[PDB]
Structures are given as structure tokens and as C-alpha cells.
Image 1 (cartoon, rainbow over the protein chains, first blue to last red):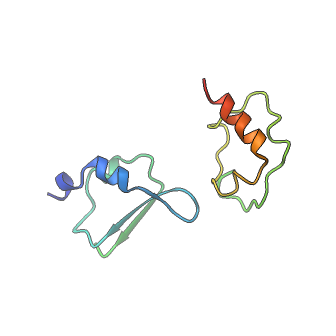
Image 2: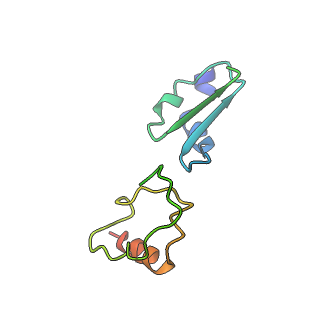
Length: 51
Length: 48
């Protein structure tokens, strides 16, 4: 249900730029890492908090 | 040049006959310190 709810497009839109000016994705208090997250080959920084 | 401790860029960087947007990989904060003319020429070279 996490994979289906967190679709690839939603994470892609949620992609942000960190201080070093590169793509970063913040996952906070999620029950896990969606499998669609690992399809973001353009991601450079992966932040996981309280998973 | 991404990740370097660069505070400024040369003003002669635009004098490159073959250089596109993809050819330069730098963070955007220090990509604007150069004069606007060379940046706009680089964007002009990016049309095709």
C-alpha cells in the first residue's frame, strides 16, 4: 500500500535541492521506503528519518 | 566542477566554441557570478 500510494510521480514532484544544490528526497516517519523511490535514477541524496 | 570550493568563475569561460549546458556541471549558486553575457550565449548555444 505504501508503494501504490507513493507513486513515482509523487516522489518525483517531492524531489528537492539540498544545500549543495543537488537532488534530495526526504522520507520522514514513513513506514518504509517505497519501491518507486528506487526508480529515481536522478536522485543524488536519500534522507530517511524515523522509518 | 561540481562540489569544488569555488567562489568565482573566470570571465573568459564563455570563449569556448564548443560548450553547451550539459558540458558544464556546476552548482547553480556559483553559476550566476559570471557576467550575464556569457551565460546567455551558452543558453543560445543550447537551442539545438
